[PDB]
Length: 107
Image 1 (cartoon, rainbow, N blue to C red):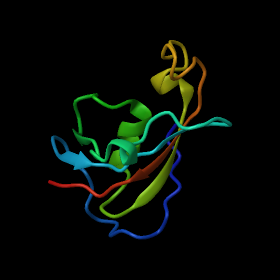
Image 2 (spheres, rainbow, N blue to C red; image 1 turned 180 degrees about the vertical axis):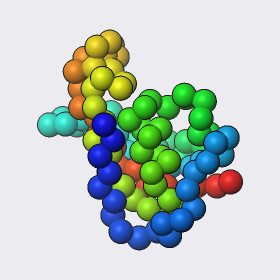
Image 3 (cartoon, helix red, strand yellow; image 1 turned 90 degrees about the horizontal axis):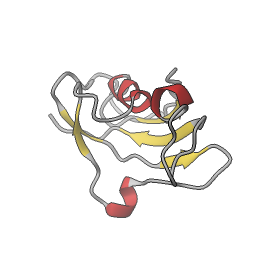
């Protein structure tokens, strides 16, 4: 389940396709918790491609549903990334992940 809450500006037509290296200013957030990851900190805005299962399903499905300039807000379910397993130290099991996702991409 990928629930999109878009902050309005963008173009609404430049959608990511397969094999397109796309650039996202992501900002992670735990529900009722602090941050855990941010591209604003490293200032290397995570040039990743679409269709190789590199990113999690709650972030990959949110990327194709956005366009250039758009600023959505992810609500990632636990069972797509870390709900059963959980990362040691960062993301616990059964965690509902929140992301501040803006798609200012290339290709």
